[PDB]
Image 1: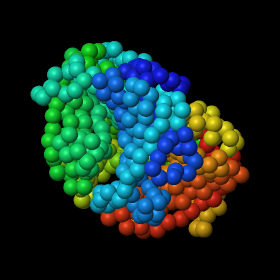
Image 2 (image 1 turned 30 degrees about the vertical axis):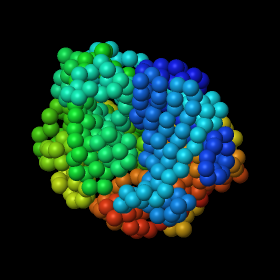
Image 3 (image 1 turned 180 degrees about the vertical axis):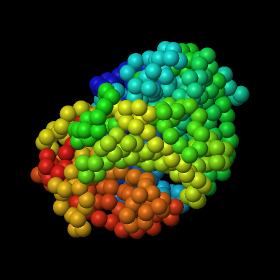
Length: 120
Length: 120
Length: 120
Length: 120
């Protein structure tokens, strides 16, 4: 696995059966809420290329650490979207694990190669 | 990991402990209602060879983005089947994540090496 | 990843941070009920060595295919146990995915290197 | 994948997209209640580096084998934390799988390279 620098490199790696890893540097991404400086790595078992213009994936992450309700069982659901221009977003939706009631959501935006890196 | 071109290549890769990845090119698969052109990659953590005649695997994928109920918590359950003649099918069943009620299902059919590719 | 032939090889692979894959050949395994000839491969993301005498792992597998209730959402929970003498067992407990009520269970027994193979 | 000996090695491996494995030797860790000698290996699909000072990850592990309620469906939720001085903790919270009610929790504390090892 190496860094996949370009959108075409990523599309090619998916078409060739490689498992993709997203690495996100939050301080290099823009958000409405302040995000503490962190690096976040996620490797979903599934990923899609939409029309040769978009790469999408998601991850439902179980936690008891979510700020919106510390100590309560929740899923942090993150949707990853990357377009052919290098513009990336991560939208995280916070769900009560027992009921599936939505507690909140927030979004970040980054650029490929900068705040949003992809490996495969 | 390389492309597993024949059914025997795939059975052998399973028998040798390799983790399998399915890459599906939807525009090369037959469906009842047309799906938009997309490439879908999935690596299940489990796989079976039945007899020496079929390979089977499945994935339960959590989503808020399913057309049948956008924004609602759902599981897209996909069952993958591949026979010794190279005929592949993917049956997706859409389930409400909190209740497990079925919301719909649909099926694609593909040919190994054409719309349906396998890596290990 | 190569075949881990001996119990010590497997323990060593775990201690060295390798991810383990179990390949089970059901026809080489003994069970109370008949099992159709199948090869089953599973790679859990967690595994344990108890004392220096047992290796254990498990996998909760979501399905709609289970014989005990075809078409109903279920988890096939498999518990894998391997002792230092090479005696392996897999106990599968079938659970309603919605309620967690137990629908049934079955067990197979195998020998390491024969019906139960391990890779890492 | 090799052993990641220092905190900087681990942070560098995450930042380069490598999937991380935690290997815990319980007998080299300190706990409130003594834990039986076991080696435990876990590979989470996500990990974070907080500031340049902490690495964190978690795993929600389904089991029927938990001492607190043997035979009952449960999630052993383990939160891993490692600081820049090499001090590691694993906090495990035991949850009823159907209801999410907390049944108990316990914690172990270890040192990087001693009881707590990391591979990538």
